[PDB]
Amino acid sequence: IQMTQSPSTLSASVGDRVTITCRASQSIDNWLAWYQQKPGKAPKLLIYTASRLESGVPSRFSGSGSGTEFTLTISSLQPDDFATYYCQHRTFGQGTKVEIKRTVAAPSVFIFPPSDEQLKSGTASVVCLLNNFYPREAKVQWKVDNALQSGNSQESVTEQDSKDSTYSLSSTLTLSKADYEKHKVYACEVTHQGLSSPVTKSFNRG
Amino acid sequence: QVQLVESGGGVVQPGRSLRLSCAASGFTFSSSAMHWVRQAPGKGLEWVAVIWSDGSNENYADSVKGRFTISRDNSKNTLYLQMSSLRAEDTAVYYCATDKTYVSGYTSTWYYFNYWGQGTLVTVSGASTKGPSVFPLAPSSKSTSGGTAALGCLVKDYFPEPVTVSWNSGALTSGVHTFPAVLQSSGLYSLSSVVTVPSSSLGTQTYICNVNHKPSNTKVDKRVEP
Amino acid sequence: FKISFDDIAVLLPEYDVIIQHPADMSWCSKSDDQIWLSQWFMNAVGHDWYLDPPFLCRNRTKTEGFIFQVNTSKTGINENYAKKFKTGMHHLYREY
Ligand SMILES: *[C@@H]1O[C@H](CO)[C@@H](O)[C@H](O)[C@H]1NC(C)=O
Image 1: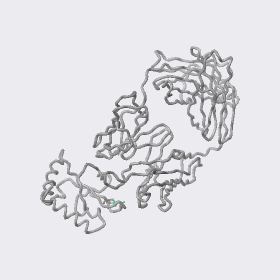
Image 2: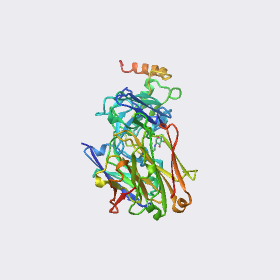
Image 3: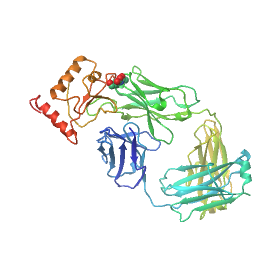
Image 4: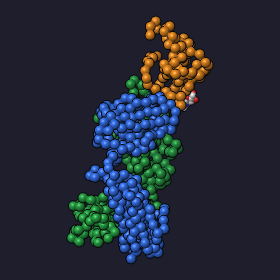
């Protein structure tokens, strides 16, 4: 019995009313449970059999539906609810992320060449930093001697900060020392909703 | 209050069967089924094992069928899980949770997990202990945006997790961001951390990053110089 | 046996036995008396085994117990069945 969720990512603010839909492959009557999860935590069950509410759960949560289609509704959204939610009958759902919504944040782009100590180690790592941007979806492309590169860059993106509610992503392009000494100009181009045009940061090997 | 503790986890080499303990107290342990669930780092949950109160009937997921086996000791209020033929894909966080077999006047295996433990971590890897390598990342002309300058430190080729990075002996927290670690194809981890400062004070303030790797007892202090 | 009517699903056709013939009834219990009473009640109510939608039962190889569930909802196609079964119980308990 496969299960599917809709949507995958959701944006809301304080006091909003949010809905999550869960569809099963075949009718399961009212055999379904709704779980809540926070980053770095343990899953806490919320809703029994799509109808009943576990003792201690806030009264602002409720569920409905039957057969193949089910829905979780939160009347008033509180700060303790920005989290991931799952619907489970046989296995778990793919997860719906209830996430804060804010204004668009212009990305800040930085570029750094590999350090000389890493050159002593024989490896080169060119880093491209994208700080204080919103929303998350941004495209990063690496250009070596104005040639597109792929399969040699790894990204690391940090979750939302509670100060400015912005995001950060560091992309590292890894090469050998010989290859790094073979090529001269290295650039990273970023494309984001908050940019009128993609912005390319380029540096030249000394 | 219902209490549950999990133990018997860490980092293990492939090919060794591991035994994990799950102690329960506070309720009628002989009259409630138990479940083992697994979450890969950064992925969703997955039900793995289930045993009913009688101790007769078991069930396991197909991905671990024939390799995992759960039993329970009702006299000692304990649950023992054995894992065999371990692969790198089994590295994850394991929870053991008590099921609710009563809903409005019926008793069955409803597959509802009601009480959970802190969760154990199992790392099926063959890597050995290795200290980290610290490389400063200094500002340049192209690393300045409207009077804002970024500095940082990259910590590479270490095992096992975790590694803690501090700044200015812990006095620098504004504008400091550490990115999550990344697994490498060589079995070693790497990560980067950065900090944003006013560009006018680059020639007047010293920035030093301290890297701590407790398993290797490594403490490395590196200064970032423009 | 105790009988209750409510809105909770405890057996599913994709998980347990779909009893269609009285011969198949033998997989639901461990005691001949319980099987005889179950068949007795079902034939007293007036269920045609090979003409009406089946009912669900649990197989003996479990340490849970004995449970059997019948669908008598009042919508869709089953509406009609709901009539039949209804009248059945109306002719036994002297009330309903
Ligand atoms: C479950 O019920 C089916 C249907 O009669 C039966 O064939 C099967 O043997 C039962 N399960 C087990 C594990 O014996």
